[PDB]
Length: 171
Length: 171
Image (tube, rainbow over all chains, first blue to last red):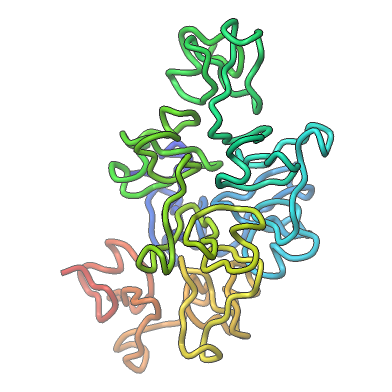
């Protein structure tokens, strides 16, 4: 029930702003000074202008390194987020990974849904559950996902903990 | 630190899936059965096909009523979310409001950033802090925002509680 630093980076629903205290709302108390994610009054910096930073709440990183929505942000020059132009990836784009766990479809584009996450999915939030570990040719997970004891790709205590063969294994 | 029903509908960062227990991760434990928001394996239904439902995590509602990202969802037919086509609103579009608290720019388009939220902003997450209440011609907040005792538009205990002149005042 806490957002931002005090909530493990959770994000408020419907673009609600996370105040500097970790609570969700709308208004200057939440959206003004110290806003953490959501519809903050001052846009967070992103991409090239902000060391390759990603925007929260799936916001588009505009060509000038500002987070937002609308033509100016998702339109021409958009450096990340749900950009108006197809985002390439996969063997098709030198092993690039989609930002924010988006699936690299079989064709080399970034999205979320059966078309990207299903059959052929290359990296990200694939729903294919392709096997890893000693159990699977000693193959590794993409996105540095933790290969669990049971030979599964995921993120979490179950995956990243006790039994993790490879991946971002807890240490 | 809880997501979904047990977290007041908080959402995980970077499209992490909220398992049926309110925890954030990646994998079948979180993304499979019972997934709540984030990159769920089965897409949540939206718009027309799902009683005007909005997609979480700012996802695009495709023409067939499915939540996602990429051409198929944000492209042609997109019924909500950060749609590839400008979303109209404001006096320009019969008082329509942007979905998910997006600002209705001075021109009648939906976004988030200074261009929409700043000067001229019509409804949503305006950063203009235009005054309400008895303190302001007895004007009301848009989006049924709570007009606080001090004459401010917001959402939260401070706004919606004790002193609320109009808006979605707590009852």
